[PDB]
Image (cartoon, coloured by chain):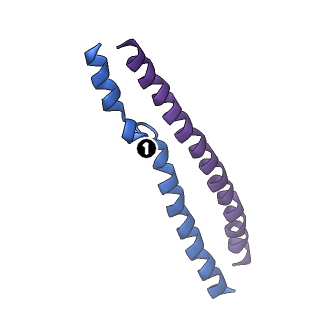
Chain colours: A purple, B blue
Amino acid sequence: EQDHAQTQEKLRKALETQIKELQIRLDEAETNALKGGKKAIAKLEQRV
Amino acid sequence: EQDHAQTQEKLRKALETQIKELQIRLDEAETNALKGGKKAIAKLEQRV
């Protein structure tokens, strides 16, 4: 059971690196998708 | 060692849920900025 605990110990640190990486990749997108649309909507405001 | 692991098996089920709600936001980035959303960009395209 210790060996089953061992991989279950290792996967926890192997899964905590997901919540550190997916969070910062999310935060990069939501600023980028906002600034992506805001620049996209402004030109079509500017040309019209 | 069993029940202490049984508490830790609850935390693994806790985080794999928490992965998916942060994973579903990666789908949300396709139209995330809804207060300036995609359709409002699309309607301004039909104007010009």
Query: Which quarter of the rendering shows the C terminus of chain B?
Result: top left
On the rendered structure, is A11 left or right of A43?
right
Q: Position of residue B2 (x, y in %)?
A: 64, 86
Task: Give the residue drawn at x 71%, y 62%.
Answer: A13
On the rendered structure, is B43 left or right of B33?
left
Q: Position of residue A17 (x, y in %)?
A: 68, 55
On the rendered structure, is A35 left or right of B32?
right
Query: Which quarter of the rendering shows the N terminus of chain B?
Result: bottom right
Work out whether B30 lies above or below A20: above
- Label 1 crowding class (10 Å Cα cut-off): few <14, some 14-19, many 20+? some
Q: Which element carries disc 1, helix, strand or loop?
A: helix
Residue labelled with disc 1 = B28
Mark 1 is on which residue type?
Answer: Glu
Residue A8 in which image quadrant: bottom right
Task: Give the residue drawn at x 44%, y 42%.
Answer: B27
In-front residue for pair A4/B11: B11
Residue A25 in which image quadrant: top right
Residue A45 in which image quadrant: top left
Count the marks: 1
Task: Give the residue drawn at x 56%, y 76%.
Answer: B10
Give me the chain letter of mark 1.
B
Work out whether A9 lies above or below A23: below
In-front residue for pair A24/B4: A24
Q: Position of residue B25 (x, y in %)?
A: 47, 48
In-front residue for pair B41/A11: B41
Task: Give the residue drawn at x 53%, y 61%.
Answer: B18
